[PDB]
Length: 302
Length: 301
Length: 4
Ligand code: NA
Ligand code: NA
Ligand code: NA
Image (cartoon, rainbow over all chains, first blue to last red; front, top):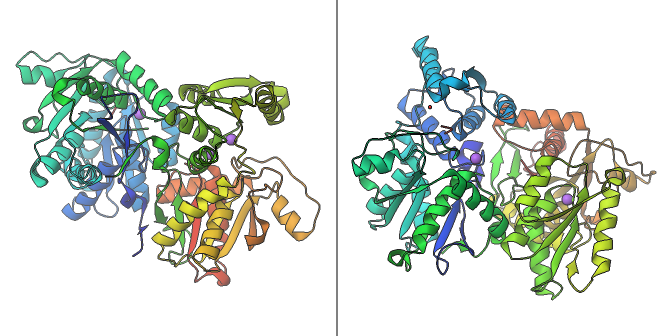
């Protein structure tokens, strides 16, 4: 009867589906704008749900401080959820952060612990572990890449929203893989709860195709790229390889060019990883196999 | 089947979040207009001014949008124009950010930079010179006078507040820039839903021209830092007759209040959002409104 | 080695 959220963490999701006019075949590419969220990214859903589970798990209690190594959207998602629910939070990340990002996080009240940019995510992960080890009783690390609350919340929210908003006629889901939680949880929701055998498509960088190489039985050779949000260089444990039907690779130039076309030709604001996801879905959408299929693309961030 | 045909149709349905560290026993609830296609409330009037000019025949295939811009309406019109296939020209002072130039150029805008010395005045002038050079192809929407600005808030923002509060809203607090938010929400609730709520306009201390006008005093506009409000005149899309109260907030209090929202509630809000909350909090502490459900517009993150 |  009333729709008043008790705090900002509960306002996650219910993101919109917008049909693309200049991609795909006869309107078969439909995007889900996860930028329309608290903290302007997909990551608000797992920010909230890992905090919510840790409270019901008993692993995060009043006075306990959150510690998480993240240079990306997960830090902002956890920061605002922590402020909204009264938790202390430490974020470790390398010193390559945008300077507006630094001011944003400390504006949110984050205890920012910076590590050497040359040590990358590995240095920040190690410092986060060190901080927790220093006093395990005082801290909790949510571990976005392994925590099941990550894919669980997309099974409970992102998936059903796609099911509901397409009146069950979604046929393909195209999602870049960072933690894998999005593609994992959406697929479980639709293939298992809704029982429809859609084509689940993971997207990764041409530069670091560790999923493609793993599935083909080849040596994995991760490498650097500029598609921020995906291509971690390993198979994250929240990516369930068994529900992946296909892997598309997009290089950084194409992702950036596609993002620019999204803004100039569709009037949609989204990050480079959204461009990657749309490049992959557009490539598929002009295949006879998918000519008749409704493709839903995850746009992870603003 | 909730699939919008273009991005302009995804406006609105923004959330109400109750504040924990403001107000009296939860009586301050904020409407987060940052959760919109171009991440401000201007998304609603960008879409509707275009929609209504199409319905009226004044905007037709081949016509181009021309508009002066200093902020969120330019961004909102840019993405609506891109989403609906219109060419759009924005006039803006050459003194604006690099970041604001690249964003508008990113949206496909034809950017024409004007004399920085002339400021906004020179950008309005250039926009008008551009429409006068070819009225056959150019259309200027004019957010301060177009009734479609307050009209969209009467049809969407207003009803959303009524729906989400089950008509328990007693007070609406909104900063005034064009006035369309406060005028359209108030009309919806007072006239369409028939509840005489208290409508509070919020303007800068530095520039209190609504307060001065209503009090019968000389109008003394001034410069301030609360981006999006305090234009220094009474905009035509502000209907003075549904305003019940005017609160004034200085730039310092607005920025401090925005930082509180961020640190204490985890809500990212622009400085004008902060001004609106500081006004609402001030009222929420008074006995008159202690038992009133107050709804605060946060225009942007 | 990413920004997630
Ligand atoms: Na991004
Ligand atoms: Na503007
Ligand atoms: Na703003």
